[PDB]
Amino acid sequence: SMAYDLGSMSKDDVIDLFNKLGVFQAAILMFAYMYQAQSDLSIAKFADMNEASKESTTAQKMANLVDAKIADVQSSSDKNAKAQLPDEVISYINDPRNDITISGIDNINAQLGAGDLQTVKAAISAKANNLTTTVNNSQLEIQQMSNTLNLLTSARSDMQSLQYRTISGISLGK
Amino acid sequence: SMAYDLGSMSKDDVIDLFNKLGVFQAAILM
Amino acid sequence: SMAYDLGSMSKDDVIDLFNKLGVFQAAILMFAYMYQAQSDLSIAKFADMNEASKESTTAQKMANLVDAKIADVQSSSDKNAKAQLPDEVISYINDPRNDITISGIDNINAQLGAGDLQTVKAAISAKANNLTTTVNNSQLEIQQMSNTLNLLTSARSDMQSLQYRTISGISLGK
Amino acid sequence: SMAYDLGSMSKDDVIDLFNKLGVFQAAILMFAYMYQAQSDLSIAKFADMNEASKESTTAQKMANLVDAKIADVQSSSDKNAKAQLPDEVISYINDPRNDITISGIDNINAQLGAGDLQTVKAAISAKANNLTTTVNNSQLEIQQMSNTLNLLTSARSDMQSLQYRTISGISLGK
Amino acid sequence: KANNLTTTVNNSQLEIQQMSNTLNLLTSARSDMQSLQYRTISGISLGK
Amino acid sequence: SMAYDLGSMSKDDVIDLFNKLGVFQAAILMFAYMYQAQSDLSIAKFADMNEASKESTTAQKMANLVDAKIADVQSSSDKNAKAQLPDEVISYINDPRNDITISGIDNINAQLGAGDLQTVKAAISAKANNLTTTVNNSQLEIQQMSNTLNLLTSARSDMQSLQYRTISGISLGK
C-alpha cells in the first residue's frame, strides 16, 4: 500500500534507506508502517466476527424456511404428518462444517410430521444465537486496538505538521 | 432444544468447547 | 492463548521481561495471566458438573427405553412374563463405571416379567436424580469465581484506559 | 537506563551536575529518575503476583494429571485399587517449597485406590484457588502506583514542551 | 506475538518528543546563521 | 507493615510528621493505620475461633480411633472384654489442658470391655460439639468489624482518588 516494503529489508538496509530519506520522513514511514501493521491486525480480527454474524443469518434463514413449511402442515385438515423440509434446508443440515445434529430420527426427506418439525426448527434457530460469545470475547481487545490506532494516526500527523513548519523557515536569497 | 449437544461430547471436548466460548457463557450453557 | 508464557519463566526473568515492556503493559500482562488462571479454574469446575448432567440424561434415556419395553408387556394378552431389555440397556447395566446394581435376580436377558421390570426402571431412573447434589456443592464457589473474574476484567480495562490517556498527552513538535 | 547515575552522587555533587546542565534539563533528569524509581517499585510489585498465578497454573496442571490417572481406575473392571500418581506429581508433592500435606496415608507410589485419589486431587486443586488473596491485597496500591506514574509522565512531558518553546524564541542575527 | 505495536508506542513517545523538537530547533538555527552570513557580506561595496 | 510507626510517636511528633508530608497523605497514613488496627483486632478475634474448630477436629479424630477399636471387640467371638485404647487416645485423655473426665473407672490401659468403651467414645465425641457456642458469641461483633473494615477501605480509596485529581490540574509552563 506504500512505496517501500520494509517487511523484508534487514536492519542495516532500513538504516541506509532512512539515511537516503530525511529525518522527518523516516519518522513518517516508521509511523505509516506501524499503522499498516496495526490496521491489518484489527481488520483480520473484524473478519472473525463477520463469521459469527454470517452463521447467525444463514441459520435464521433456514429456520424461517422450516417455519414456512410448518405453516402449511399446521393448517392441514388431515393428521399433521405430511411434511418435508425444503431442498435447501436438507443440504444445510447434511453439510459437514456446521455440526447441526438435530433430530435423532431416521430418514429425513420422508417424512417428519408437524410436531417433530418443531424440534428441527428449534435446533436450527438455536445455533443462530451466537452474537454474545463474540461480544464477550472481543471487547477488551477492541479497546486497545481502537486506542492505539487513533494514538498512532494522531502521532503521524504531528510529524507532518512539524515537517512543514521546519522547512517554511528557510528564506532563499535573503 | 439448544445449540450444543453436550450429552455426547466427552470431557476433553467439553473443556475445549467452553474455552472456545467465554467464561460467563460456559456457565450459562452449564 | 497469549504471547509470553509466564508459567515457566523464573522471577528474575519475569522482572527483566517486564522491564523490556513498559510499566502499564506489565500490568496488562499480569492481569491477563491472572484472568487466564482464574478462567481455567472456573472452566475446569464447570466440566465437573456436565458430568452430572450427562449421567442424568443417559440414565433417563435408558429408563425411557425400559418404559417403551413395558408398554408392550403390559398390553400383552397372555401372562405378563415375556420381556427382555433392549440390547443397549443391557450394556448400560453391565458396564462397570456406573455402579447400577438393580435386580438381585438371575440371568438378565432371559427374562424378567413385566412387574419386576418396574424394579429395573426405578433403579435406573433413580440414578438420574442427581442435579441437586451438584447445586448444593457448587454455589459458594461460583459465588467467588464469578465475583473475582468480573473484578479482574474490570481492573484490566482500567489499566488499558489509563495507558491510552497517558500517551495522548504527548504533543510532538509543539 | 539513563546517562547519569544519581543513585550514588551526594547532594553537593548533584547540585554541581545540575548546574553543568541547564535549568529545564535538570528538571527532566529529576523527573526521569523519579519515574524510574516509581516504575521499579511497581514492577517489583507486579512480579509478586505472577508468583501467585504461577503457583495456580502448576497446581492445576498437577490436578489434571491426577484426574487423567483417575479416568483409568474408574473405568477399571476390577476393584478400584490399582493406581499410582504419575512420576511428576510425586515430585510435586515431595518438594519442600509447597507445603502440600495431602493424604495422611502411608507409602505413596504403592498404592492409592481410586476413591482416596480424589483426596489427593482435591488437596492439590485446592491450592490452585489463590487469585483472590492477591486481588484483595493489591488494589489500593495499584491505585496509587498507576495514578502517580501517569501523573509523572505527564509532568515530564510538560517540561519538554516548555524547554522547546523557550528556545524557539531566540532569533539569531535579527 | 503479532500484537506488539503498543509496547513500542508506550516506550517511545517522550523521546520522539525531544528528538523532534531539538532537530527542528537546530535546523532553524543553522538557517539563521546562513541568512546572517549572506547579509553581512552584502554590505561591502567594492570601489565606492 | 508500613513506613512510619505511629504507635510510639507522641502527638507533637505526629503533627510535625504530618506537616512534613502533605495534607492528603496525612489522611492516607491516618486511614492506613486505622485499617491496620482494625484488621489486627479482627484477626486476633478470628484466631480464637480456630481454637474451637481445632478442638473439635482433634476430639473427632480421637472418637474415631475409639470407634475403630470397638469395631474389633464387637466382632469378638469371646466375651466382649478384651480391649485397650490406642496409645494416642491415652495421651489425649491424660493431657491436662482438656478437662476430659470420662469413665470414673480404675486403671485405664487394662482394660475396658466393649460396652463401657461406648462411654469413653461418647465422652470424647461430646466435647467435639462446640461450634455453636462460638457462633452465638461472635455474630454481633463480626457484624461491626466487617462493616467498619469495609467502611474504612472505601474511605482510604476516596482519599487516593482525590489526591490524584487535585494534582492533575496543575499545568506546567502554560
Image (tube, coloured by chain):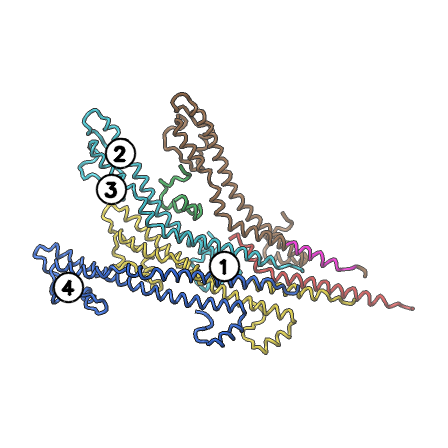
Chain colours: A brown, B green, C cyan, D yellow, E red, F blue
Q: Pointers 2 and 3 in contact (CB under 8 A)?
A: no
Q: Is residue A167 magenta?
A: yes
Between discs 2 and 1, the one toward the N terminus: 1
Number of residues whose C-alpha sits closer than 10 Å to that of mark 3, classed few (under 14), some (14–19) or many (20 or more): some
Residue indicated by mark 4:
F103
In the picture, which quadrant includes the C terminus of chain D? bottom right
Mark 2 vs 3, N-terminal side: 2
Cα–Cα span, label 2 and label 1 = 59 Å
Majority SS type along the magenta span: helix
> Which residue carries the number 3 mark?
C100
Disc 4, SS: loop
Question: From the image, which quarter does the N terminus of chain D lie in?
Answer: bottom right
Q: Is residue D7 left or right of residue D122?
A: right
Q: CA distance from mark 1 to mark 4?
A: 64 Å
The CA distance from mark 4 to mark 2 is 58 Å
- What is the three-letter code of the residue carrying label 2? Val
Q: Label 1 belongs to which residue?
A: C27
CA distance for labels 2 and 3: 15 Å
* Distance between the alpha carbons at the discs numbered 3 and 1: 52 Å
Q: Give the residue type at disc 4.
A: Ser
Q: Could you confirm whether marks 2 and 3 are on the same chain? A: yes
Give the number of the disc on residue A35.
none
> Of circles 4 and 2, which is in front?
4
Disc 2 is attached to a residue of which chain?
A: C
Q: Position of residue A4 (x, y in %)?
A: 63, 51
